[PDB]
Image (cartoon, rainbow, N blue to C red; front, side, top):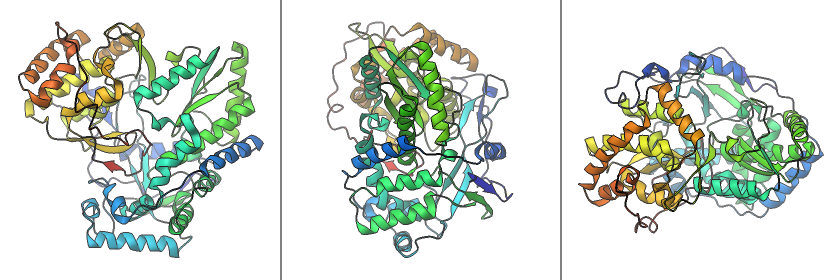
Length: 566
């Protein structure tokens, strides 16, 4: 079966697309080699289409069947709730793509009669029609990156496939509780999204330390969404049906599976038929949960076929990492070859073959790795970091153009204890917000796929809560880390680290001479910059009235919004 079939009609943009980082009079503040930065457009969609289109061969065995059963036994434990129309409407983001039927996201969140009436008709139709394929729109996504080491090497745009706004609200009524609760019930501590960065590190380290003689490797599949088969999607549904569910929820799930999740027709922004899909749609509520369960299922069965000792896995969508008991250098290498052969049989071949690693700091997963620094007292602290190239390019682009979503904010949040995030990101953006007086204006950013509204004045509290005060006192970063960061700054033309120390004291001062939330930002966010460092004490409001539901599950491609955690 082919992952996609194409008619020849083109994948079209619904509006003008910027590809080059226009000559900004402030982004230079950050980076000078503009030509290194680019955004993907519709123009490279055909290149992506050829990467993503191929026949899938899949052969299942006893290990696969044993593991599926164990998963279903755990899922049987779950009781899921049907969301009411109102609750599902509130989860919709304010700028979600409007409906083909004459109402938008503003209308849905306001519970307008025309929106609610169309939403009900969609719901009833899921009960009355068990089989007609549901329409979806295919689009080229606009994402920014830094040019490939092979100068001129560029990533073609990724493709996003999604049903109408009305269908998306119904997916939430039937499946939001399921997608937010079942992964953890089935996968235990192996479910990645239940962890904040601080917790993910803790789990990686204790697990590594749990081994007598550790071995580990990251495994990334080549175009995972396209490797997902009709069979995989139906197995996913068999796991969801093990929950206790209301009858209408049960039928909605059955209909959604057959009419949308397994495949359907592709329509461009002009209303023309582009072709047909028989693999995972990247923009449905179930894609994170579905990919996570499917990845876990195939990998767990693969270790058994390969006979790997005491494997513990950590899965986030298609990102997989595993740490087992080493059995000898030669042994290990041959076990992976085996593991890859089994994954391949299960319809999940790798992009780059995996490599056994015997140093935890060398494993890269979710585009990140564990590194080591020291805190105030000097007690080796572990934390998560990543190559900063993409984050810095995106921050440059966001300085020059107002984007709906601000990755820089999410990056400060998720990587606040990092060297680059503190010296560069915090300094650059707080000077800017200072300049325009936007410390109040809340900004939209996203964590693990969900869109969250956050007011920059609350970062100190958020950071303390997630990372602990160590994040405000780390200091003797590793050499490999400092080298990677400085090498990245040269590549892009970002001013050397020692330069930022200077701008920091300035901003910091302008923030203290401000008081309120402003002043506290100045005290904790820039303590590393002051010559006379002070002793930071736990924040009041922070470690108290702070909201959660932040690290429960992944919602990438899911159209999920929460405007909480101020």
